[PDB]
Image: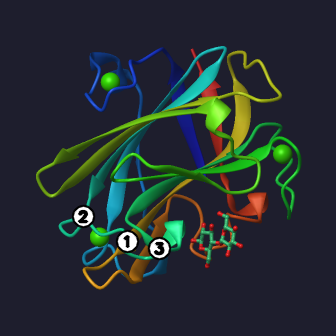
């Protein structure tokens, strides 16, 4: 429900900056489809500065696949932001869904834009690391500012079928259209 992100500016390249160690790690344990022991999950660290929100997601996934024509059905990570944290039941102008797969290919849901999304992906033993920067659209964050946030891992099998949907705050697979399913992220100094 609630987490924090330390102020900081990491380099987007898929490598783990020392600074990521200064912020808490959250886990995607809100299951909508699949299970924690059998499907893709991520260990996530979050940082922020006046211009972007930064996300480091270490994904556990032994089988990588992107054969499905649906981007949400390819092994990928989705990031959700609610800048004014209104927790509405639908997307406002400030709300957004961003997506990037293990090949660092970006796709977008409502509100998401490539002009505000920089990403890098590096494969690792047993999975992959996603490092992203999301440019704020409507706000200029200050310490103790609270935004709505969620991160989801889509797990596809060798058959190109999505078998897992696990996020941090949403076990109902509605984050793509319902910000009220996002958790709260306090931007701290
Ligand atoms: O992302 C835009 C796209 O979303 C599709 O819904 C996905 C959603 O993106 C994802 O977060 C969730 O896990 O799965 C649903 C599908 O069940 C939606 O169907 C598209 O119309 C829309 O363009
Ligand atoms: Ca880095
Ligand atoms: Ca909003
Ligand atoms: Ca997979």
Picture quadrant of residue 83 = top right
Does residue 15 appear left or right of residue 177 in this picture?
left
Residue to which mark 1 is pinned: 155
Residue in the image at 77% along x and 64% along y? 178
Distance from the alpha carbon under mark 3 to that under mark 1? 7 Å
> Considering the numbered disc 1 on the image, is that residue within a helix, a strand or a loop?
strand
Q: Using a 10 Å C-alpha cutoff, classify the residue at mark 1 as few (fewer than 14 neighbours), some (14 to 19) or many (20 or more).
A: many
Picture quadrant of residue 155 = bottom left
Q: Are marks 2 and 1 in contact (CB under 8 Å)?
A: yes
Residue to which mark 3 is pinned: 73
Residue 61's disc number? 2
Q: Is mark 2 within 8 Å of ligand 4?
A: yes
Image quarter for ligand 2 equals: top left
Does residue 7 appear left or right of residue 101 in this picture?
right
Nearest to the observer: residue 55 or residue 116:
116
Location of residue 85 in the rendering, given as x and y in whole percent from the top left corner = 80, 43
Position of residue 85 relative to residue 21, above or below, is: below
Distance from the alpha carbon under mark 2 to that under mark 1? 8 Å
Residue in the image at 32% along x and 73% along y? 36
Residue in the image at 73% along x and 20% along y? 141
Distance from the alpha carbon under mark 2 to that under mark 3? 14 Å
| Colour approach in the figure | rainbow
Location of residue 112 in the rendering, given as x and y in whole percent from the top left corner = 69, 46
Of the 4 image quadrants, the one containing the C terminus is top right
Nearest to the observer: residue 60 or residue 133:
133
Nearest to the observer: residue 189 or residue 8:
8
């Amino acid at each position: 429900m609630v987490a924090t992100a330390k102020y900081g500016t990491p380099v987007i390249d898929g490598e783990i900056d020392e600074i990521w160690n200064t912020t808490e790690e959250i886990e995607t344990k809100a299951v909508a489809m699949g299970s924690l022991d059998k499907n893709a999950t991520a260990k996530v660290r979050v940082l922020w500065d006046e211009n972007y929100l930064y996300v480091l997601a270490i994904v556990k996934d032994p089988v990588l696949n992107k054969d499905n024509s649906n981007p949400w059905e390819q092994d990928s990570v989705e990031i959700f932001i609610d800048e004014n944290n209104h927790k509405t039941g639908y997307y406002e102008d400030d709300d957004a869904q961003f997506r990037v797969n293990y090949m660092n290919e970006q796709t977008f849901g409502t509100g998401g834009s490539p002009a505000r999304f920089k990403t890098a992906v590096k494969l690792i033993e047993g999975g992959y690391i996603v490092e992203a920067a999301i440019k704020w659209k409507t706000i200029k964050p200050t310490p103790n500012t609270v935004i709505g946030f969620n991160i989801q891992v889509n797990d596809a099998n060798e058959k190109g079928q999505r078998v897992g949907i696990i996020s941090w705050s949403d076990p109902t697979n509605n984050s793509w259209r319902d910000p009220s399913k996002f958790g709260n992220l306090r931007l701290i100094k």
